[PDB]
Structure formats: structure tokens, C-alpha cells
Image (cartoon, rainbow, N blue to C red):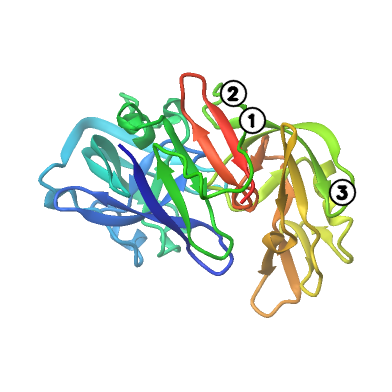
Amino acid sequence: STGSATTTPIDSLDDAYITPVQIGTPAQTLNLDFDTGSSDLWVFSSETTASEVDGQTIYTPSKSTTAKLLSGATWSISYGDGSSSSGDVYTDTVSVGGLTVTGQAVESAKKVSSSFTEDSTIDGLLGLAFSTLNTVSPTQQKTFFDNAKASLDSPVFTADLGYHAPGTYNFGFIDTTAYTGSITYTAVSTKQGFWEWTSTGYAVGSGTFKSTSIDGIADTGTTLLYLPATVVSAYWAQVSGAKSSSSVGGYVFPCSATLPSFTFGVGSARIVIPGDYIDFGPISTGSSSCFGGIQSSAGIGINIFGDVALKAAFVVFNGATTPTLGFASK
């Protein structure tokens, strides 16, 4: 089997992407944030504290003839941005782009932090990291990908995120029309539960490539590109007037600037992030100071190849017995 679903930016800045997911019988369609940096599929629901729901679409398990409470199961999760959610668990039928999993753990939010409440466009998350990170207790649950894997024509999914435009998540096949040149595959460590790999270096604009190993995770659920402070300093030093602002929380730059591209290495291959991808607009409405799309990972504890980087590529998440990551230009 295969699946193919369109993923759509939630706003003009590509702060995140939502992908429609059918849950239950009859289908309830929720728009979820596909997140290769986590492993819980959780949804706003009929169980979510009412004051914590503000415009999201909710999953109502009582209206699904295939929903079954997973007795005793709870979940609780915190993300790198400090947001969190928690609740209980049903199993139900979940389909993505024509691909169907029966008995998928659907984690029903009883509580969500303000960040989620304040974002009316995201009805939940669908984790695509490794199931070892799944927070369901006392019985850890599998991701949608993990549950689908055996049925898929090939044990892969791909992320083709658009820049200010819709893109595509495919399950079980590689769309050879979706990228240019070849796909360069690179080794993955699953030791921390993530799609963790090692970039072979970087360049800033038309500058020479710096060969250097950068360990990081391929994380569709993170907006920006988080890299070591040395790298990020090298990048912003090429932008007149750019500075790190503690008050704002990262590198800002004059909105009047033209940003240079950023290249990262995948083995011998190179992915170029156009400068425009790195502009996340005014720090506040009307401000002439703009927020940078490349930020320091210092104090995160890990480098994150978030959407800024991934949207510049066609990315293959290869869940073979030995998982690997593939990157192609597009």
C-alpha cells in the first residue's frame, strides 16, 4: 500500500505545516502537524478542557464506531519549545492520504498548554520519530508509520515541504518526479529516538564550503534551522546590521536586508537553502527588525534541521531495518 497527502503551511511564514488526517468511523478529519521529531499522535478532542480549545477541530471518540478506549493508558508530552499536552488514549482507524492503519493509538488531549490553544490551525500532532519516544504509559504505543510499515510497498515516507506553498507527505513510495538529480543517503542513529544524522558541513552564500561534522535531527515539527553558535555567527556576519538579541530571543536582522543562501552538506552532496527561506519577518507587527530563520542550538543540546532546512529538499525517511535519511534537491 501507499499514502499521499498534501501538507499546507499554517500561515504566511511557514511557521508549521498541517496535513489532513481521517480518524474514526465515520471519518473525522483533523489537520495535524506531522512531526519527525516526536512519536505521539495526539489530538484535540471532546475530552480537552473547554477553556483550552479555541477554534480547533476536535476528535469525538464517542461518535466513532471503531474507537476503543485503551484502558489505563495515559500520555504526557513536552516539546522543545516548552509546550505540552496530556490525556488518555483510544485506538481507532487512522488514514493518511489513502493509507489506513487500524488500531492506531490516538492520544486524546485532556490538557494542552497555551501555545496549542492559541493556534487554531493545528488540531494535533502526528509523530514520525521512532516509537521508542512514544509517551503512552504503561504500554508504549507505535507511531502511524511504524504501524503501517509492513503493509507499505517500501518502508519509507518522504517529506516534500513547500516554501510559502503546499507540499507533500508520501508513505511507502518515492516519487521520482518530485526532485532533481539523485537522492543522497546518509546514516542515521536511532539511539536518541530521532532521525539523527551528521551533515558534512556548510557554506554561507557564495562562500567556500567548510567541511565539518554537524550532528543533528531531521525535524519537520521544528520551524527553524538550529545549528552551532559558530556556524550561525558565520552566517549572520554576512548580513549588515544583524545581531543576536537576548530580548527578542535570537538573531534579528534589518527587514531591508537581502539574505544570503545557506548550504548544508549531505555526504558529498549539497542542499542550498535560499536566503528568502531564512526570513521570518518582523519580530512584531510593523517593526523593521526581522527574525532570522537560522538560530543557535546552544542551550538546546542538539542541532535541529527544521523546516527551514528540510523545505529546501526532498527528504526520504527510510525506515528499513537499518534506517537512513535521503536528501535530494528539488
Q: Is residue 190 above or below residue 269?
A: above
Q: Quadrant of residue 145?
A: top left
Residue type pointed to by label 3: Ala
Callout 2 amino acid: Ser
What SS does tag 1 mark? strand
Which mark is first along the chain, 3 or 1?
Answer: 1
Residue 242 in the figure: left or right of residue 271: right
| Residue at the left extreme, as displayed | 65
Residue tagged by mark 1? 197
- Mark 1 crowd level (few <14, some 14–19, many ≥20, 10 Å Cα): many
Which residue is drawn at the image coordinates 44% and 33% (left, top)? 156
Taking the image as shown, residue 274 lies to the left or right of residue 106, namely right
**Which of the pair 155/45 is nearer the observer?**
155
In the rendered image, the vertical position of residue 224 relative to residue 300, given as above or below: below
Q: Amino acid at mark 1?
A: Trp
x and y percent of residue 285 in the render?
A: 64, 77
Q: Is residue 136 visible?
A: no
Mark 2 surroundings: few (<14), some (14-19) or many (≥20) residues within 10 A: some
Separation of marks 3 and 2 at Cα, in angstroms: 27 Å
Label whose residue precedes the other's in the sequence (1 or 2) = 2
Q: Quadrant of the N terminus?
A: top left
Q: Are marks 1 and 2 in contact (CB under 8 Å)?
A: yes
Residue pointed to by mark 2: 189
In space, the residues marked 1 and 3 are separated at their CA atoms by 22 Å
Q: Residue 74 versus residue 159: which sits nearer the camera? A: 159
- Residue at the disc numbered 3: 234
